[PDB]
Image (cartoon, coloured by chain):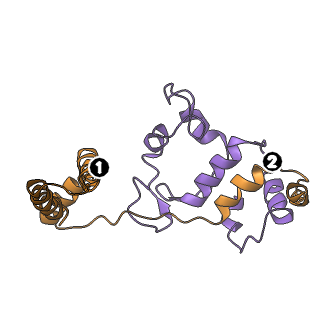
């Protein structure tokens, strides 16, 4: 009953629903840029940052940090607690 | 926007073929050489005849959208704008350039 009430949009004198859904994106649209910087003394870092190899490694660290966060059990050994405490420092330093 | 540094409307037309090569077949062209399909098709339909290296985004994306489905022959190009002003929402005077 909701779908039938939603079918009363009778604008289909020449174009179907798909042309009323894909062509409308053309009327209201704007291209957004990428903000290329200058002074290649700084662009050297920019080129390094956004790369396939960079994101992957950086997105794998999160996976590793999540795995580290998902091992704290009950009544854990003192050496285990200290190891996790110093391992959290490593991830915090990498992210900073 | 890969070859477009800002949002100042018109952009260079020199690398349009290379831009279209990166697009998938459903929106772009076939995987074959552009020398037979894309080269002729770029001139086949209607374009806004602006300067040599000034072609704006809302006339190219709209052209590809109109080429995708319900393609119409020459002479009745104004019929498209009539349909937009009779069915499509408020143009906000933005379709004056897209008409040509």
Residue at 55% of width from left, 58% of height from top? B57
Assess disc 1: are there few (<14), some (14-19) or many (≥20) residues with their C-alpha within 10 Å of its C-alpha.
few
Q: Colour of chain A?
A: orange
Residue at 56% of width from left, 34% of height from top? B25
Q: Is residue A86 left or right of residue B13?
A: left
Dot 2 corresponds to which residue? B75
Residue A19 position in % (x across, y down) = 76, 51
Please give the chain letter of the residue carrying mark 2.
B
Q: Is residue B100 left or right of residue A52?
A: right
Q: In terms of image quadrants, where is residue B71?
A: top right
Assess disc 2: are there few (<14), some (14-19) or many (≥20) residues with their C-alpha within 10 Å of its C-alpha.
few
Disc 2 secondary structure class: loop
Residue B64 position in % (x across, y down) = 63, 47
Q: In terms of image quadrants, where is residue B81?
A: bottom right
Dot 1 corresponds to which residue? A63
Which dot marks residue A52?
A: none
**Spatial CA span between label 2 and label 1:** 59 Å
Marks 2 & 1 on one chain: no
Q: Is residue B100 left or right of residue A38?
A: right
Quadrant in the picture for the N terminus of chain A: bottom right
Report the front residue among A2 and B80.
Answer: A2
Q: Is residue A14 left or right of residue A36?
A: right
Q: Which residue in the rendered view is the most extreme toward the front?
A: A75
Quadrant in the picture for the C terminus of chain A: bottom left
Vertical position of residue B38 compared to residue A73: above or below: above
Front: mark 2 or 1: 1
Please give the chain letter of the residue carrying mark 1.
A
Q: In terms of image quadrants, where is residue B27?
A: top right
Residue B38 position in % (x across, y down) = 55, 34
The purple-coloured chain is labelled B
Residue at 64% of width from left, 66% of height from top? A28
């Amino acid at each position: 009953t909701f779908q039938e009430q939603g079918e009363k949009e009778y604008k289909n004198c020449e174009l179907d629903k798909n042309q009323r859904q894909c062509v409308e994106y053309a009327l209201k649209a704007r291209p957004l840029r990428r903000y290329i910087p200058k002074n290649p003394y700084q662009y050297k870092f920019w080129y390094v940052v956004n790369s396939s190899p960079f994101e992957y490694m950086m997105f794998v660290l999160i996976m590793l940090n999540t795995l580290c966060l998902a091992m704290q059990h009950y009544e854990q050994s003192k050496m285990f607690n200290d190891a996790m405490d110093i391992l959290n420092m490593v991830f915090t330093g990498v992210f900073t | 926007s890969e070859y477009d540094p800002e949002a100042k409307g018109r952009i260079k037309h020199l690398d349009v073929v290379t831009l279209l090569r990166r697009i998938q077949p459903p929106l772009g062209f076939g995987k074959l050489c552009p020398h037979r399909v894309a080269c002729k098709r770029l001139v086949a339909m209607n374009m806004p005849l602006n300067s040599d290296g000034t072609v704006m985004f809302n006339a190219t994306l709209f052209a590809l959208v109109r080429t995708a489905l319900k393609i119409k022959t020459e002479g009745n190009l104004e019929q498209a704008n009539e349909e937009l002003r009779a069915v499509i929402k408020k143009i906000w005077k933005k379709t004056s350039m897209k008409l040509l």
